[PDB]
Image: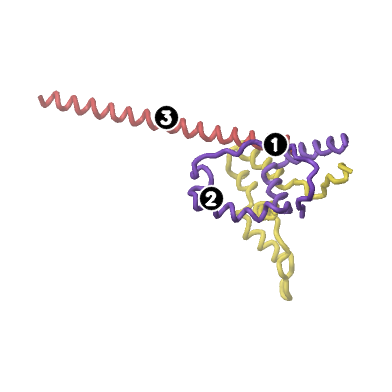
Chain colours: A red, B yellow, C purple
Amino acid sequence: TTQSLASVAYLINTLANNVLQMLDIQASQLRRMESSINHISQTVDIHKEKVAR
Amino acid sequence: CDLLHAAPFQNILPRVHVKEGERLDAKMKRLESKYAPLHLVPLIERLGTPQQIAIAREGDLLTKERLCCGLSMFEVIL
Amino acid sequence: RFVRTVLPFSQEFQRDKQPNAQPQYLHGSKALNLAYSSIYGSYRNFVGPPHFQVICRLLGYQGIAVVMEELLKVVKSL
């Protein structure tokens, strides 16, 4: 039973760490995506004003 | 009115009062140094992505150049 | 200032029907709706600088150019 309890706790810890790591990289990718979208939106709006001028 | 609000970020300073004892050049240089952080282009140039530099330069060019700086259209209509 | 004339020579505008919805969609509560209508009722009897500046802000530059070109065409036809 002690061996089983130690193994179960070890499995839970590694799974939790892996999930947290996966979530963090996903958030980092999303933040990088947001910056690119903002740059594209800024580029579009300056392009439109030049045509209006 | 719109251009008036963009003066701080374009190094557009007014004519400050100068009295006996000091010259215009020294006062203007001190005043420019005081408002240096507000100026945008060099702050982006020193640190910032090239894309940010290009966007800021284009935005500054569009804002400074407008149709009340020696441009009219009533003559064309006539 | 521009003011309305007398004995109109044209009555063919036939504008679209006004949209009607709950008070919330327009100026919040019913009590607030009456106050705003009264406030803006002073601008109905004339057209002046306040109307022109709002038009400039809303239309930007594309609206001005297209309006000017259309007015030129109207003058040409007349």
Q: Earlier in the sequence, mark 2 or mark 1?
A: 1
Q: Is residue A41 left or right of residue C45?
A: left
Name the foreground residue: C68 vs C78. C78
- Give the labeled residue for mark 1: C14
Between the C-alphas of marks 2 and 3, the distance is 47 Å
Q: Quadrant of the C terminus of chain B?
A: top right
Could you confirm whether marks 2 and 3 are on the same chain? Answer: no
Q: Position of residue B36 (x, y in %)?
A: 63, 55
Q: How many marks?
A: 3
Q: Position of residue B38 (x, y in %)?
A: 61, 54
Name the foreground residue: B59 vs A25. B59
Is label 1 in a helix, a strand or a loop? Answer: loop
Q: State yes or no: discs 2 and 3 in contact (Cβ < 8 Å).
A: no
Q: Pointer 1: residues within 10 angstroms few (<14), some, or many (20+)?
A: few
Vertical order, B37 against A20 (above or below): below
Vertical order, B13 against A28 (above or below): below
Between the C-alphas of marks 2 and 1, the distance is 26 Å
- Give the labeled residue for mark 2: C33
Q: Amino acid at mark 2?
A: Asn
Q: Pointer 3: residues within 10 angstroms few (<14), some, or many (20+)?
A: few
Q: Residue at x 47, y 34 (%)?
A: A31
Q: Residue reaching furthest right?
A: B78
Name the foreground residue: B23 vs C18. C18
Is label 2 in a helix, a strand or a loop? Answer: helix
- Give the labeled residue for mark 3: A26
Chain designation of label 2: C
Q: Position of residue C16 (x, y in %)?
A: 65, 36
Q: Is residue B27 left or right of residue A21?
A: right
Q: Amino acid at mark 1?
A: Gln
